[PDB]
């Protein structure tokens, strides 16, 4: 169980790294969606024109 | 109880890995969509003109 607990803490570090990668990738896509929203604003202006 | 803690955290790890693969493929779709959005933004500026 000592070996299992040490592997469990290592896998908890894996949970930390995986959730950090997921949240950072989600923030990058939110910024890309913001860029897409800017593009949509441009498209809206184009539609008005 | 600690072995059950390790197993439940492993359950969270496998659920997160399934989400990593499926949502990663959708993220590659979003990458392509972001590229398309950038090109479409350029085309939207040209179309607004």
Image (cartoon, coloured by chain):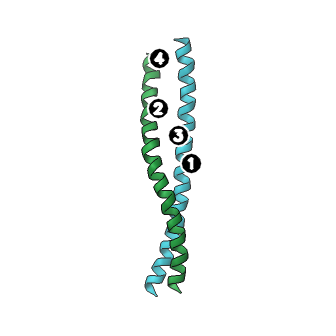
Chain colours: A cyan, B green
N-terminal of the pair, mark 1 or mark 3, is 3
Separation of marks 1 and 3 at Cα, in angstroms: 9 Å
Q: For residue B2, which numbered disc appears in the image?
A: 4
- Please determine if labels 4 and 3 lie on a single subunit: no
Callout 1 crowding tier (Cα within 10 Å): few <14, some 14–19, many ≥20: few
Residue closer to the observer: B10 or B22: B22
N-terminal of the pair, mark 4 or mark 2, is 4
Do the numbered discs 4 and 2 sit on residues whose CB atoms are within 8 Å?
Answer: no
Separation of marks 1 and 2 at Cα, in angstroms: 18 Å
Task: Kindly state the secondary structure of the residue where label 2 is placed.
Answer: helix
> Residue B39 occupies which quadrant of the picture?
bottom right
Task: Kindly state the secondary structure of the residue where label 4 is placed.
Answer: helix
Q: Is residue B33 left or right of residue A17?
A: left
Q: Mark 4, mark 2: which one is toward the viewer? A: 2
Q: For residue A24, which numbered disc appears in the image?
A: 1
Do the numbered discs 1 and 3 sit on residues whose CB atoms are within 8 Å?
Answer: no
Residue A44, how many percent across, how many down?
Answer: 45, 79
Compared to B4, does A49 lie above or below?
below
> Residue pushed farthest top?
A1
- For mark 4, name the chain: B
> Which residue in the structure is indicated by mark 2?
B13
Task: Kindly state the secondary structure of the residue where label 3 is placed.
Answer: helix
> Which residue in the structure is indicated by mark 3?
A19
């Amino acid at each position: 169980v000592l070996i299992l607990e040490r592997q469990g803490h290592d896998k908890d570090l894996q949970l930390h790294q995986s959730q950090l990668e997921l949240q950072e990738v989600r923030l990058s896509y939110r910024q890309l969606q913001x860029x897409x929203x800017x593009x949509x604003x441009x498209x809206x202006x184009x539609x008005x024109x | 109880i600690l072995e059950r803690q390790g197993h439940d955290k492993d359950l969270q790890l496998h659920q997160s890995q399934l989400e990593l693969q499926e949502v990663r493929l959708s993220y590659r779709q979003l990458q392509x969509x972001x590229x398309x959005x950038x090109x479409x933004x350029x085309x939207x500026x040209x179309x607004x003109x």
